[PDB]
Image (tube, coloured by chain):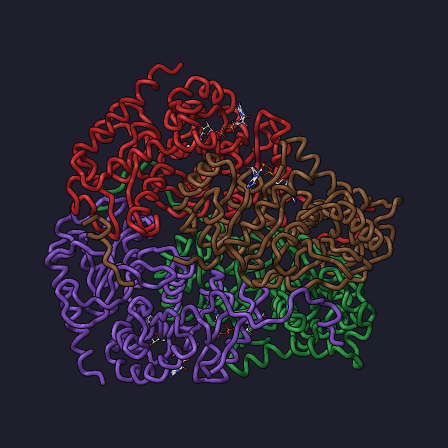
Chain colours: A green, B red, C brown, D purple
């Protein structure tokens, strides 16, 4: 006999069990590990799987997390370059790639392996350019559109609500405002929805968002766009904020909360867009994924920007093969 | 045609999805609502179902909880006397029945509460055949046996809250004695959740330091530390609280949430809960009492084999003999 | 030597975030359990005049200490047990009856915690918050009435039920007096910043297909309905008080619809307390959000302030 | 006026407000950020301050954390190379300095990190003279002694992260062997956080069941369970992780938040952290190593007296001689 046999008397019979809320993180770079630690911190999964092509670094990150198991509530942390380790995931976060032509080749291999072992999963795409790669993930996986989610402008909106909170001196959760469309240079700041305690700030300042504004809100939007670039210049990358926002998305889905997030969904047929492109809009997230999108009253220039972004994205998307 | 339809544009096709971690609390008395509020506070369920025979109270308790949904993370709270509201529960907490009057043994509640369980235990597994049943109603050890006979479920899915509360009271009294946190005080109250509970002095330790080695008189009448009085306080704790406020509820609610956390998060933590202990320490009958057990998503998968001293084994069999007498005469 | 001296070798107790709950009825214990569940304090004190029930409640909470992160739970009818509290939650009571209760409780609170923040929960909460402010001598930023905080939570729940989303994703403010005369600020009701009144301009009027005036009446009637069904309400208010305490003890500056002294706002000339969007942090209630309310909403605020002052003007000492 | 003045009407006068549970992290490398993200994720502080000599990276880490403020409960995140930004800290975590190269002993870093601490520690105490210092930089036991001598703080306010991490690793490996949660496993690694650490086999247990009483060969060479191998894996764990990913950070960040939680919440939980152990187990000089210690809002208030076997005392005193041998040659 062994010490396990002499100390522990089995009551329930032996079993190989399938986890209930397994999460897989593809890519253990700065972003992937930031997602992993935030996911573990919120006690969101009973099995965290890591996957990467760098076998040594992957094993090291896995061991480092396992050594903290005493302080967590995740009884199984696993990792391998073989995608069988991701089997039966509920949510798969894809952060792999360089930081379009190069990332599409990565996704052409990764996405089929994901749905081969987790056909019922939800896929959150984080790799840049995220709106284009969410389209690639949707096409390659064959999954319905409510199960392919691009992180999109969820982070851009968090940055905007932080800068707005700094102007007013209240908590970012008490400041409301949505950055929508394309994650990056061409995002759209819906000024009509910017409010505090239901007080529409554009009604107190109708020049909000224009070039003659005593409060300079166009500069705030510019700082949201330039935030990634400035932080990248200072520390080489960004990871902590995106990791926190991904865990926020996973919380809404795994707990089935039906909270509204500015994430990227397939917006063909909305606001006059005719191509299959992914853009960020207010979306309802729950245990089934992205089940609903909020219909908004967007001004002409806001719709014009969405149409322009959709044209720019599709112009890249149409030349991709297989 | 509806504000929902004007504002909410569908992306996924309309369906009805089963809950992932639904929990039912049967009986919304003092204990049932303390379990419910602790479960909700820890964000342990995506659907909470309540059942009671008092329709008006049951509805008001559902509504009160729903009014706090802004501060919670449970998107569905439902309640009805019909057990169809409990369908597809992962865990069913049973707190219905009568409680102790002032100075009344939990063993005096057997017959009244067995009759309650014969009505409700069949209706539970009818609508939740895949569920785990946590017995809270007293006497918990006997009612866990009764639940294990009436539902047909395997042993690993029928769990009595048992001495998880009793050990929590013991570790608190330990903690006050030594000046450290109760989580840093280790000790196990086992056997009956009642007057015949057994303090396992051989395992009472701080940071791996056996306190019985420091004081061999631990638990005897020639003890300068009077550890026997600490065990008496644990036994007397419920009677003292009932005399002061009429009942107990907050501590047991926290204890039940603690068990549910280990199972729904699949942690495999060890809790002293009441299980079928036949063939252990000389127990010859299907006696239910508390032993250190491993809880996870499957329920009660394992029991920890202990190396008890002779005085402790005798107290355990003495506790089991007390429990077997009432069990064997149950219709 | 003792076992504590044999086992514990010394190397080296003022609480950092002490909270007192006054009154251990249904509401007080609901506040206590929600405060403990969120690990908001290192020392919880309870005070009531029913000595035996107070002791039993204290012992019951202590027995669950293993599952909590609050190392000191104390209780006593004597207010010395409340010494040096950061926040005091007042839930005691059964107007004339409750004023005689507060004339006793409030001076004892400030005697033993002269720098505390007081949260008044007892009804009528707007009158009793004013009474607390006068008796305590505290600046108005340290006297907070729970006010319409719970009402706005009930409103957002009913919105969420109407739309199928989480209440935290529904936004709308119930302000003014906590009773039947609360104001629904329809112009702020929004989902994802989409103004629901601009989609339904008849929001709040009599001829409204979405019947928003009825949702406002359900907010008022729900308190009466729960009371008729289970005898009282407690779980929702306990969660809402714990949410307020979280904003202050974590210094978050989140906005809550709590009751503050609104003299000089919206034409109100008397010293009355009404619910407005207020910024709560470690200093207490440091700011109020300036809104541009409609005429009838301001008219209801001035009517409530008149009814409140009509009762307040005849209170002695 | 500005938008802030037209929208927000002051109820309270403006005031200089001192933070309530401010934490500073010195050194924003792999370990410092892992601590920060763990501190922020558990909502342990209302003000996080960051300090480093790399001004650009320091500001980038500050902005990156600030961009996640919507998902946090920390209203103030600040960063500067000037220690005035650390003022009024309750706890200061020092993770600055050089780390092990592949295959390098922690003790080989002592002279480089002592010179780093000679400038860091005085600046910390100038701006937070009433703080607790958690030393993380290696060799942590010696640098805790150095910190204690440079700070002038009482012993109960200078803490080395110590074997809190080695013990978590040991309890994890024990858990994988037994199939239960590490929190239900109990075992202590004491002494130096390094090659000469001591595994207290006499205190290893599960539910109070002494595992050395089930296997008296535990820790020796003729052991069927190969427990000496488990301790070897703990000692070698850092070198193996460094070989694979170049460093370690996630587990120590979780360990540091664990200590901070016990202290800021005043819990008096027991952790194996590095403290001044002169006069214990025959140790003659002011050396720091890990023993079970009670941590609360005052810091390290108490040490647990253990009944160590003669072999365990010898290994512990051997570890103290090794540390003191390096401690003598400091200037
Ligand atoms: N959505 C957002 O807002 C947001 C914010 C930050 C970063 N990002 C994006 O996330 C991505 C991750 O950035 P990072 O800082 O973690 O970079 P990183 O270099 O630290 O991580 C890249 C990882 O991808 C892995 N990888 C490379 N090729 C692979 C393949 N064929 N299969 C599997 N794995 C492979 C590498 O092993 C590496 O671990 C970047 O593309 C970045 O642009 C997005
Ligand atoms: N395990 C423990 O450590 C522990 C601690 C405290 C109490 N308890 C036990 O928990 C039980 C609950 O006590 P309480 O304080 O809530 O008493 P209570 O009277 O407040 O609650 C009893 C509730 O059960 C309901 N009920 C009765 N028969 C029912 C039936 N057939 N179906 C559905 N509901 C029914 C009643 O309507 C009532 O609401 C008692 O038996 C008590 O002894 C156990
Ligand atoms: N503002 C809100 O949203 C809201 C919601 C519910 C209830 N309430 C109010 O909260 C109060 C509490 O209601 P409850 O259901 O707990 O009532 P309850 O009868 O259950 O509790 C009242 C408690 O106050 C205590 N008490 C009486 N006089 C006292 C004194 N001088 N000092 C200390 N304690 C004293 C009593 O001992 C009793 O325990 C009620 O007055 C109710 O109107 C407010
Ligand atoms: N105690 C443990 O269990 C444990 C576990 C892991 C690492 N460590 C130790 O923690 C330390 C940090 O490791 P790391 O991987 O974060 O290193 P790193 O190289 O990633 O970061 C070190 C940081 O310290 C900063 N720094 C250096 N000198 C400084 C000074 N004089 N003032 C201010 N900042 C200064 C550097 O700019 C750098 O950002 C190492 O010494 C390592 O050995 C200890």
Work out whether residue D190 or residue B126 is closer to the camera in this orientation and state it. D190
Nearest the eye: A212 or B220: B220
Instruction: Residue at 14%, 62% (x, y): give it.
Output: D281
Give the residue at the far front of this rendering. Answer: C317
- B241 up-or-down from D34: above or below: above
Quadrant assignment, res B28? top right
Can residue C223 be spotted in the picture? yes
Vertical relation: B81 (above or below) B88: above
Residue A271 appears at what percent x and percent y?
Answer: 79, 64
Please state which of residues B186 and D151 is positioned toward the viewer in this rendering: D151
In terms of image quadrants, where is residue A164?
Answer: bottom right
Q: Position of residue C243 (x, y in %)?
A: 58, 53
Residue nearest the viewer, comparing B141 with A292: B141
Q: Quadrant of residue A294?
A: bottom right
Task: Please provide percent x and percent y for residue C50.
Answer: 50, 36
In the picture provided, is D17 more to the left or to the right than B179? right
Q: Which residue appears at 61% of the width and 39% of the height?
A: C93
User: Quick check: B21 left or right of C2?
Assistant: right
Left/right placement of residue A174 relative to residue A214 reads left
Residue D158: image location, x then y, percent: 32, 70
Q: Residue furthest right?
A: C207
Residue at figure coordinates x 85%, y 44% from the top left: C209
**Picture mark count:** 0
Q: Is residue C164 visible?
A: no
- B199 to the left or right of B84: left
Tell me if residue B114 comes above or below residue B272 in the rendering. above
């Amino acid at each position: 006999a062994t010490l396990k046999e002499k100390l522990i008397a089995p009551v329930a019979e032996e079993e190989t069990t399938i986890p209930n809320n397994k999460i897989t993180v593809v890519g253990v770079g700065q972003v992937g590990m930031a997602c992993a630690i935030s996911i573990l911190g919120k006690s969101l999964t009973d099995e965290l799987a890591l996957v990467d092509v760098l076998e040594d670094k992957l094993k090291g990150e896995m061991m480092d997390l396992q050594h903290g198991s005493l302080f967590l509530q995740t009884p199984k942390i696993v990792a391998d370059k073989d995608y069988s380790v991701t089997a039966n995931s509920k949510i798969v976060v894809v952060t792999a790639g360089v930081r379009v032509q190069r990332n599409v080749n990565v996704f052409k291999f990764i996405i089929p392996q994901i749905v081969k072992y987790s056909p019922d999963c939800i896929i959150i795409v984080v790799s840049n350019p995220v709106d284009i790669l969410t389209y690639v993930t949707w096409k390659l996986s064959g999954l319905p559109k409510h199960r392919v989610i691009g992180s999109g402008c969820n982070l851009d909106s968090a940055r905007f609500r932080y800068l707005m909170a700094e102007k007013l001196g209240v908590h970012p959760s008490s400041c409301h405002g949505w950055i929508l469309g394309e994650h990056g240079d061409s995002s759209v700041a819906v000024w009509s929805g910017v409010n505090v305690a239901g007080v529409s700030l554009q009604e107190l300042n109708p020049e909000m968002g224009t070039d003659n504004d005593s409060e300079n809100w166009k500069e705030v939007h510019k700082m949201v766009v330039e935030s990634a670039y400035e932080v990248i210049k200072l520390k080489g990358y960004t990871n902590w904020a995106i990791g926190l926002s991904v865990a926020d998305l996973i919380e809404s889905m795994l707990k089935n909360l039906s909270r509204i997030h500015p994430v990227s969904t397939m917006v063909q047929g909305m606001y006059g867009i005719e191509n299959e492109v992914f853009l960020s809009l207010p979306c309802v997230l729950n245990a089934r994924g992205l089940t609903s999108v909020i219909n908004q009253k967007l001004k002409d220039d806001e719709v014009a920007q969405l149409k322009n972004s959709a044209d720019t994205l599709w112009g890249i998307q149409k030349d991709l093969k297989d």
